[PDB]
Image (spheres, rainbow, N blue to C red):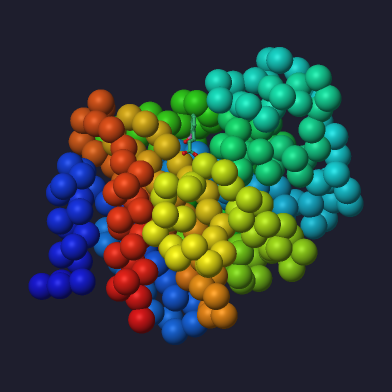
Length: 264
Ligand SMILES: O=C(O)/C=C/c1ccccc1B(O)O
């Protein structure tokens, strides 16, 4: 029997679906795992790793991040509020990356995906950092279908957390790029009701959300700096068996609380 897991099982039963959690305390090595190796749809959470992949490329391309991109209306996608706002001015690669991370801007994400060689190019970047689980197969908005049993556009909570650690705290990015990735995550605007709702107000948090909508499917991953302590990295993913089942931000926050409470 796994007593640590019982509150998570109760939570997912109340929710009406499945919850996957992995959390790592980088100071002690302590972890919390629940369905941590199961696949869940990435939804928009892929956009954080997209931004990291762009940052990695910028390490060999002088001024890539500062390069202006003058996209047209044909690049726009529903829920592209930053891209629409800057349509008449253009945006730099860095601004597109920040929009994808901090507003889940769909047009910005697809524009950057194209620069990287599409979903397979982002998947290849994740392979290059040692992530063998992540797979992106489609673009926005098709990647949100979240069909039960479909492995397209999925990863696992553990693989997400391990890759997030490598990119934000480890050596997968050069230091200036690691810091930029962290800065973008800390400026996210979409996650106030998810992992951020689980952490004490004085702790610093960088996160990236995902919401497929269908099949009760939504998620969040975060790096969390408790004041004066080594950071925690964690991922919380959800799904549900019926297409019209609704996702729950409260369930994501509640799972994150249990993860923080369960850490040594
Ligand atoms: O970050 C979120 O919670 C939502 C992102 C989003 C919004 C509209 C359409 C697609 C997505 B995404 O999850 O792919």
